[PDB]
Amino acid sequence: EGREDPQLLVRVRGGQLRGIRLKAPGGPVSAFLGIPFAEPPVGSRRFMPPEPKRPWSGVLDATTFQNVCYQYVDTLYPGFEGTEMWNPNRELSEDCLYLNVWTPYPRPASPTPVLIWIYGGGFYSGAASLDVYDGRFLAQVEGAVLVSMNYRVGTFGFLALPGSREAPGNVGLLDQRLALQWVQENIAAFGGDPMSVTLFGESAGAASVGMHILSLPSRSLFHRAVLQSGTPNGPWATVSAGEARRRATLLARLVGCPNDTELIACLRTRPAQDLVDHEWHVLPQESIFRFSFVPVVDGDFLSDTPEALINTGDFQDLQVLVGVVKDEGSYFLVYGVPGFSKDNESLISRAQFLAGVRIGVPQASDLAAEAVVLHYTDWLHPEDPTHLRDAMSAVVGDHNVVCPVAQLAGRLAAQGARVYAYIFEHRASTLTWPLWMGVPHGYEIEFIFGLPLDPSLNYTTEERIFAQRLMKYWTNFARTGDPNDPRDSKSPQWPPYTTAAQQYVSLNLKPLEVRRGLRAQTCAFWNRFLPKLLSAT
Amino acid sequence: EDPQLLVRVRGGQLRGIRLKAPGGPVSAFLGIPFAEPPVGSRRFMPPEPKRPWSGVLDATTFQNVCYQYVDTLYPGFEGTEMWNPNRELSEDCLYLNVWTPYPRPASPTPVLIWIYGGGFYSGAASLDVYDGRFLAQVEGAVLVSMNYRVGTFGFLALPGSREAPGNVGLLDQRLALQWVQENIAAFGGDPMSVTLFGESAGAASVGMHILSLPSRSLFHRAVLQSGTPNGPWATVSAGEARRRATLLARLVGCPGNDTELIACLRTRPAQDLVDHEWHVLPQESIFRFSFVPVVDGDFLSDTPEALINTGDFQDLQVLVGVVKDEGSYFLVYGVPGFSKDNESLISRAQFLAGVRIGVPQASDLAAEAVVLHYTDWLHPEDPTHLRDAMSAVVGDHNVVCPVAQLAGRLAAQGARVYAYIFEHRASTLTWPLWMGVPHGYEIEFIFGLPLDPSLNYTTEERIFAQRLMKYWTNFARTGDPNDPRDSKSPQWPPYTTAAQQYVSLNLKPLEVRRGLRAQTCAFWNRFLPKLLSAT
Ligand SMILES: COCCOCCOCCOCCOCCOCCOCCO
Ligand SMILES: CCN(/C=C/CNC(=O)c1ccc(C)c([N+](=O)O)c1)CC
Ligand SMILES: CCN(/C=C/CNC(=O)c1ccc(C)c([N+](=O)O)c1)CC
Ligand SMILES: *[C@@H]1O[C@H](CO)[C@@H](O)[C@H](O)[C@H]1NC(C)=O
Ligand SMILES: *[C@@H]1O[C@H](CO)[C@@H](O)[C@H](O)[C@H]1NC(C)=O
Ligand SMILES: *[C@@H]1O[C@H](CO)[C@@H](O)[C@H](O)[C@H]1NC(C)=O
Ligand SMILES: *[C@@H]1O[C@H](CO)[C@@H](O)[C@H](O)[C@H]1NC(C)=O
């Protein structure tokens, strides 16, 4: 060294790092990108829990994002911004267990609360290096230390032969836990406070945050949690051990690997792409919002089902922020329900609605399906194509996100937790999906991370002010367990969600509005009635 | 002797009586026999036409009430006593009443025929709230009402037997309808314009005449207030009617083929049968009645649901409707926690228990479905919400949703259908405020009782009653309740399956609404029948 920026050089447990000085709209931030936190889970380590990264020699260059975990790449609308913004933006590789750190420049004086991001992507996709997860704005404007990790997805992260030693399952969650242990040991070297760590994540990343809440070994690694449009409970975030075994065994057959040791050994000789090319083909029914390889209820990482664990756990110590976007379901309709396209209005027939309910609720018996169709039909206009389109969206969003979130918020609150709930209702002026899709799944993230502050990106001025308000809420929650500004009592206040009052806030361009009941009538259908109907039929 | 009060019908001569209505006199012919008294060997048998008589028969007073249970829940309280028999009880009760204008109509006049309710176990055409003088005087109508047998006497059935074939109380109604055909022209009535109207069990009876071909040639239009032939209480299967009759016979000590069983029942004094009438229901329930019309394959060739689903109604005009709180009345008669004397704020546990009583045929899963649909999950334990939800369950299950189903099926199969909800609560009502507008408390307005200054109704209620009398009689005259001379825009539109328009009847002008509890009635009419079948 000697000629380098002395404020970009840092030592962690594994050796010396060189970061890079990035420009944010209000000034510089420090980024340390591509820090390895595990041994590369390659070859004999495929499907195995991660091992801590062995120390390296010299100064590791941490100025660029590392490889994205090998994954399926979405090809539905090739070249369309609305899909490509989620696709891998670095080389696909099984050598992908790296994390990223953004801090103020120069690094902070006092120990600073840490935010750890866990990306979504249905547990089959995602990367911490995507533009919408850019930590520079929270670091610069709010002074936060922000960490994001890559974790294995798809078969590499979640293929399980439950009870085997060579594929115990949930190793993608163990990747996340190892990054959390890395933060505990090393974040102080960046000025981060290991005693104030807040997890946040969206969709499967939110479900992941919920699983760390529910898994004893993770609970000593963080203090507060944010779950955006996802829950560990609900119909897609976990599978039984029997179902995971069935899916792993079918996938093996499809790639030519007909005793668990021999089966897994043959799988480890298969090229990564061959596994990806058959991943989607093991689902038990025609479905949407269902993913082949997800966390497994193993009796280990998850000692029981999430529903059992949230129904009986002690959460006196927990502060959580949870919420949903306005149109959770619309995104999923164009990836499978006949009649839906991003390129037309998707006005569907009653027949297409019934067929779509079977795909969106693939576990429903005929009676359960008919119950869904009866609840969601508008009986003054039972065949109006616009209502049917919007009802199909609401079926998929309610069943997979809103009512699982309502259930989690209600159970956590009844069990001692401080819960804050929101609905996010603003549609980005820059959104490229059609207007009928409303505010789709995932389109609050760019506002939480403060992308509207980047002048290049063509957001409106009000969207810039809105983004800053949101970053305030999130970082205030990280700092204190309370999204409200300890000062500004003039601005309306965000009350806790309670079982008795069920209050939550609207997040849009106008000041906070408090509302009661998270789709309370409809979610009683999903959360109380439907399980008893399915058990009887 | 007043010649306006002397009439010759086919059976002989009648003397009526001149009555005072607020606007002038009316002619009343009360207590006209239309059948041989159904006594002794004729108990449980179809009625027979009245034999001719000599001289002038005195038709100046109401005749006996058909033998029936007398309600004793709140003795001496007007709200219950107003429905109790106001003449002596007798099985010799097959008489009818005719109100005409004074002087007798110069041209043939549309006829309204009232069929009273009372759950098929009670009722009488002599009740003060069925007083026909106001409709006759103000609207110039000819009004007819008949007594028909109720309880075991009208509906005890050993299906297939010769001595108790079932439905004889409905045959009583039909005989009176044919009497109107043969005789009403002598009073100035027009036998070619006959409108039936009735409430609760009487509306269900009107519906059953719609669905039985021999009655169709006896009337032209129909009004069904707060009751339907379809739905859970108005009929029983042949198998269940046989079970109840056999059980009642067991209870009164009658040991055996149908002939001997019915013979021993015929020896029992009337009160012996009434004493056990209420003891044969298969479950603890409300809004269920032991002896009601039976699907015999004769009067009712199939179930009302099958018949309204397949019938052709292209030349039928129907007016149907409900009151705002169909269910509240029934809660104080069985549901623990409910009383006319306190606000009946109930717990959640009492709500669950009430749903089993109010939907006595529901499985556990179906009862859970009802509870979860009617709970307000924003206030799941609020006593006021739970009370009002209990009322709504009973009213929707038994009246509102069956009415919506009938209106939609009739409209879809060519019928002209007009629909209403009645939302004015009488200023004179004696039931508590939490019961709202209870089952049966639109009748006094249709019949025009507010026009009597002595009953202390408000001036707005007099105006409102006149408006309703005009809807009903305009519908009787034309099949359309809209005034053919009122040219303002508060028009009552026909109910259709597409737009589902109905109107609210209250002190303010007609307002048009769409959808008669469409979402909730879809649960009752579409989902729950599939659920009870499956599990
Ligand atoms: C406007 O009132 C609607 C009150 O809905 C309560 C919803 O609770 C869920 C309880 O589950 C009941 C089971 O349902 C089966 C479906 O039947 C049709 C529902 O019919 C319309 C619902 O909108
Ligand atoms: C927000 C909606 N997303 C698209 C949803 C539809 N595609 C899938 O569900 C899917 C796709 C591919 C695989 C391998 C898979 N699997 O194995 O689970 C599941 C955005 C990219
Ligand atoms: C509008 C409600 N009415 C009262 C409802 C409760 N009583 C009954 O239902 C009842 C009462 C008696 C008998 C024989 C019977 N049966 O066997 O059919 C049913 C008016 C007072
Ligand atoms: C929209 O487009 C898709 C495919 O292009 C098609 O299947 C669907 O029927 C279309 N919908 C409408 C309403 O045109
Ligand atoms: C923003 O708008 C300008 C047009 O003035 C355009 O040239 C530029 O490419 C846009 N940038 C983005 C990110 O949309
Ligand atoms: C109303 O009174 C009845 C009898 O007096 C009683 O059984 C019932 O519990 C009371 N209801 C309430 C809500 O107190
Ligand atoms: C009407 O009110 C008066 C009291 O001013 C009373 O004397 C009379 O009996 C009341 N009539 C009825 C029918 O209640």
Image (cartoon, coloured by chain):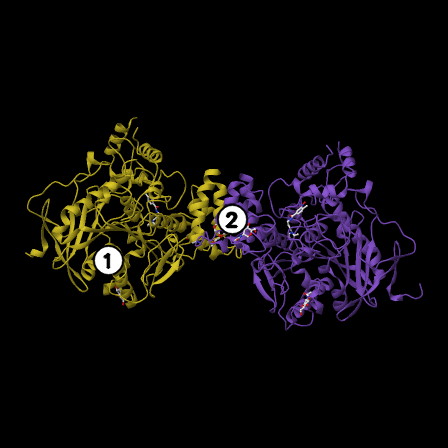
Chain colours: A purple, B yellow
Q: Which residue of the protein is positioned furthest toward the top in this rendering?
A: B256
How far is disc 2 from disc 1 in space, using C-alphas? 46 Å
**Image location (x, y in percent) of residue A521:** 52, 54
**Image location (x, y in percent) of residue B169:** 25, 41
Find residue B304 and report its image quarter: top left
Find residue B174 and report its image quarter: top left
Q: Which residue of the protein is positioned furthest toward the right in this rendering?
A: A2
Mark 2: amino acid: Phe
Q: Which residue of the protein is positioned furthest toward the front in this rendering?
A: A79
* Residue bearing the label numbered 1: B473
2 and 1 marks in contact (CB < 8 Å): no
Total marks shown come to 2
Question: Residue under mark 1: which chain is it in?
Answer: B
Disc number placed over residue A357 in the picture, else none: none
Question: In percent of the image, x 65 and y 70: which residue is there?
Answer: A460
**Image location (x, y in percent) of residue A285:** 60, 41
* Residue bearing the label numbered 2: A353
